[PDB]
Image 1 (cartoon, rainbow, N blue to C red):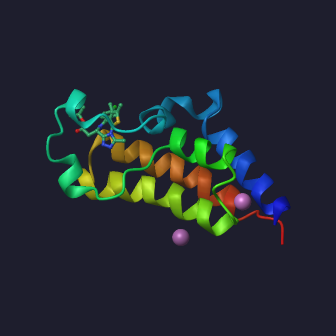
Image 2 (image 1 turned 180 degrees about the vertical axis):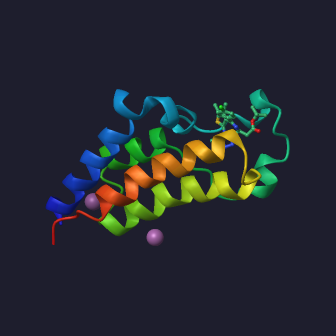
Length: 110
Ligand SMILES: Cc1sc2c(c1C)C(c1ccc(Cl)cc1)=N[C@@H](CC(=O)OC(C)(C)C)c1[nH]nc(C)[n+]1-2
Ligand code: NI
Ligand code: NI
């Protein structure tokens, strides 16, 4: 399951890669709610998450198993789906990146 964590790290690297940058970019760093004018963001989203935070957690050996990693990546998407109306541009981006994630996560070594 060090094997499994390596698969997770590969997925993370892919999500951050140029291949997917057109839709991944909003998820690169924490939402800066004040900068964006989203003064209700932290009232609605109790547990912010983004790919830089996932990357720091992976580098620090925070995640003890693949399931913990996947829960954080999915939290990041869920936050987007919670905050924004379903027809929003950023939601379309989240759905695309989540498709990339879920398909490759499903290829986890046993
Ligand atoms: C850096 C980031 S983080 C992010 C966004 C941006 C820009 C965008 C966004 C990204 C891409 C495109 Cl084409 C459009 C919007 N939207 C906001 C919510 C919003 O409504 O913000 C505006 C007030 C529209 C700025 C949002 N929700 N969740 C996330 C992760 N984001
Ligand atoms: Ni550990
Ligand atoms: Ni989960």
